Amino acid sequence: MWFGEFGGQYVPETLVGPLKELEKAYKRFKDDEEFNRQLNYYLKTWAGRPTPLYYAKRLTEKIGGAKIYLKREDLVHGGAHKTNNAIGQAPLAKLMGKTRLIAETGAGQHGVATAMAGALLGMKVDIYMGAEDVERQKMNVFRMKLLGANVIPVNSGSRTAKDAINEALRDWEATFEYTHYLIGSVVGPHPYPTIVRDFQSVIGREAKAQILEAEGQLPDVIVACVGGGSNAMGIFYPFVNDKKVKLVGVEAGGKGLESGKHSASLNAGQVGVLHGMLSYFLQDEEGQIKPSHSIAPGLDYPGVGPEHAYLKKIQRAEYVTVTDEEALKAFHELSRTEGIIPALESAHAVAYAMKLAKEMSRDEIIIVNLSGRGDKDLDIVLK
Amino acid sequence: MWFGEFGGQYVPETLVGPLKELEKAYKRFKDDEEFNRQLNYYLKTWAGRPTPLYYAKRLTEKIGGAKIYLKREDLVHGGAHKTNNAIGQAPLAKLMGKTRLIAETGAGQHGVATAMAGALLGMKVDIYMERQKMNVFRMKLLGANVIPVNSRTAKDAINEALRDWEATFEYTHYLIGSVVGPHPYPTIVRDFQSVIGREAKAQILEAEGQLPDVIVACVGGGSNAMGIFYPFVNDKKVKLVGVEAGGKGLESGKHSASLNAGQVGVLHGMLSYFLQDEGQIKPSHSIAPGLDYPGVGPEHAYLKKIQRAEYVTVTDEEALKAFHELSRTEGIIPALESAHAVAYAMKLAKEMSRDEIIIVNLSGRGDKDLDIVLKA
Ligand SMILES: CC/C=C(/N=C/c1c(COP(=O)(O)O)cnc(C)c1O)C(=O)O
Ligand code: NA
Ligand code: NA
Ligand code: NA
C-alpha cells in the first residue's frame, strides 16, 4: 500500500471492499500459471511482444557521446505501452466476474488500449474523457468508437484528465459489482500503483535481456518520460536493485518551470492527496489542485505515481524536466535521423537523452524508453 | 524475366542499362552473407520482425467454421508490410553507389516506407504522388520531399518517377513499391516480402502442427499477397486466394479488379492485366487507396493462368463491414486494403469445417483510414 510516505487508499468507505477484492484476486492470479500463460499469449500474438531494442546509430554518432538505445514500445499493438497494462487487467476483471470496463483517458491511448482489450474479451467499455481533451483528441475518440466503446465527455471542473478520473471514481462507486475500473497509470488507490507497475515491468525485463545481448553489460542510464509514471516504472523496476544503473524520469517542462505552465509534479509540486493516493501534485497557493499543461497530452496529469515520489525521496531515481520546444525538436530529430516518428510524450525522454549523451563518453550506454508512436500527434506538431 | 508469358522488360532502350545493372547487383547481393545480416538486423531491431500470427478466436467462433488466423503485418514499423520492401531495396541502392531514392505512392504507406528507409540510411528521398493526407505530412517529417503532380492521378506517379529515373539513374535508385514494373522489380519486391510467408509457415506449424488450408490476401499490385503466398506455392494442398477491390460493384465499372475484369496488355514495362476501355488504360477506384491501381503484378497473372491461385473480389461496402467487424470483435483496426481480405475470409470460413485453417494477411493497420471510414 505504501512506498515510504506515499500511496495509501484515500477513497470513500464504499470502495474499501472493492479494493480489497481486487487485491485478493490479484494476489491469487499474479503467480497463477494459467493466468500468466494467457497473459503472455495475448502479449505475444495480439500485442506483438517482445518489442525490439534499437540502436539509434546515426543519432549517437551525430551527438558524438554515449550510445543511445531505444526500447521500441511504439511498436506495441495500439502504438503505446498502455496496451501491456490494459490486457493485464481486462482478463483479471473477467475472472472476477466483471462484464464492463471503465477508464479515464487524456491522450486517448489508454482509452484506446482499454477499448481494444474490451473488444477482444467481449466486454462493455465506457471511457471517461475531459471535454477539452475530447475536442483535442478527436481521432483517438474515433478509434475508441470504432472499437465498440462509448466515450463519455466530462463537463465537470476543468474538463480534463483529472476530471475524467473523478467521474470514473464516481461511476465505479455505483457500479463496482459488475464494472472494473481499469486505471491506466501507476496512480490511484492501492493496489493500482503496484498492479500497473507489475504489468509494465515486462518492458524493463525485455530491455535488460536485450541490452545484455547487444553490449554484454547493463546500461549506465535509463531515461523515460513521466506523466503518471507507468512507462517509466515498467522500464525502471527490473533495474532498481542494479545499483550502478542510473534511472532518470523526464517530466513535462511545458513553456518553462518559471512559466507556471508545465506538468512537473515531482520537480515543482508538493505533497497532497488526490484520486486515492498521497503523492506529489501541482497545487495552488491556497491549497487546491493546479491546472497542468504540456504539448504532449499524455503528460498533462497534475500528479505522479507514489512509487516515483518514493524513488525520488531515497534518491534512487533522478527526475528532470524538458520543455515543449525541446520535445518538439526531439520529435523532428528522431524522425529525420532514425526514421522513427515518436509520441510527443516519448520525445521528452529522447530530448533529455540527447543532452546527457553529449556530456557522457563514447563507451557509455543509455536506454531511452520510446513509449509510443507519433501518429496521434501530427496535427499538434503542425502547430 | 517472365512468369509464363507475363512480366518481361518492355522499356525504352535508355532504361535497359540501368535495369541490367540492378539485376546484376541484386544477383551479387541477394544471398550475400553481410547484406542479409544488415537487412535482418534492421528488420528485427528497427522494423520489429517477426510479426505475430494471431488466432482470431471470437471472430472464428461467431462465424462457426474454419479457424481464422491473422498474419499481423499491421504491427510492422510504419503500420504496413510496405516497410519490408523499402528496407530491402534501400541498402541495395546504397551498395550500388546511389545517394538518392525516388518512388511513387498510392495510399502513402510506400511513400512513407520509402521515406523511413531513406531517413534510416541517410539517403535523399523524393516522392511522387489529400485522401491519405496524414501520410503526406509523415513523409515531410521524415525528411523526404513530396512532389505533387500536375491527369494529376496516382498512376501518373509511376509515370513521373520513370521520367526522373532516366536522367538520374547514375546516383538515383527508383524504389518501386509493389510486384510490378519491368524485370527485375516484380522478383525483387516479392523476394523482400517473402519474409511474411516464411514467418507464417513456421508460426502456423508451431501453433497447429500443420500447413493452412487457405491463405487469403488482398491484391492491389500484389506484393503483400506474393509475400505470404510464395513460400507456400510448392505446398500443393495450401489453397491461395487473392482478393481484389470490387469497388462499387463489378457491374458499376468503378473497381480495381485487374485480374478479374481487366485485359492483358503492356504498361510500366510489364506484360500483365490492366483495366481497359478501345484497349486503352482505364481509371480504377477503391475506397481502399492502396488497391486503387488499374494494373496488377505479372506473377499473379501467371498464378491465375496455371490456376495455382484463385482471385476473387470484395466490394467497398463488404470491406467496410469487415473493418468494423474486426475492430469490434478482435480489437484490431485493420487497413481498408487488409479489410478486403478479412471480408472474403469471413464468407469462406462459413463454408469450411471447424478443423480447417485460414491465414489472412493483415497487411496494415487502419489508422490511416479513419477519416474515410468516418465519412462512410
Ligand atoms: C493520464 C492520461 C495519460 C495517457 N497517456 C499517457 C502516456 C504517457 C505518460 O503516461 P505514463 O507512462 O503512465 O507516465 C507516455 N507515453 C504515452 C504514449 C502515453 O499515452 C492516456 O490517457 O492515453
Ligand atoms: Na514483434
Ligand atoms: Na504529472
Ligand atoms: Na489492381
Image: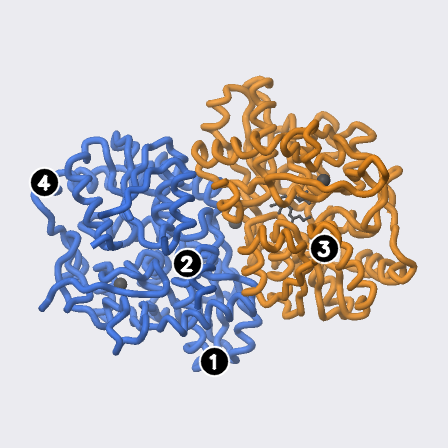
Chain colours: A orange, B blue
Dot 2, crowdedness within 10 Å: few (<14), some or many (≥20)? many
Q: Secondary structure at mark 3?
A: helix
Q: From the viewer's perspective, is B360 left or right of A3?
A: left
Chain hosting mark 3? A
Q: Which mark is residue B14?
A: 4
Which residue occupies the foreground of this view, B250 or B299?
A: B250
Q: Which mark is residue B259?
A: none
The three-letter amino acid code for the residue at tag 3 is Ala
Residue, disc 3 = A164
Q: Which mark is residue B363?
A: 2
Chain hosting mark 2? B
Position of residue A310 measured from the top left corner of the image (x, y, whole percent): 82, 35
Rounded to the nearest angstrom, the CA distance separating label 1 from label 4 is 55 Å
Query: Is B179 rendered above or below residue B92?
Result: below
Residue, disc 1 = B353
* Quarter holding residue B287: bottom left
Q: Dots 1 and 2: beta carbons under 8 Å?
A: no
The three-letter amino acid code for the residue at tag 4 is Thr
Picture quadrant of ligand 4:
bottom left
- Dot 4 or dot 2: first in sequence order is 4
Disc 3 versus disc 2: nearer the observer: 3
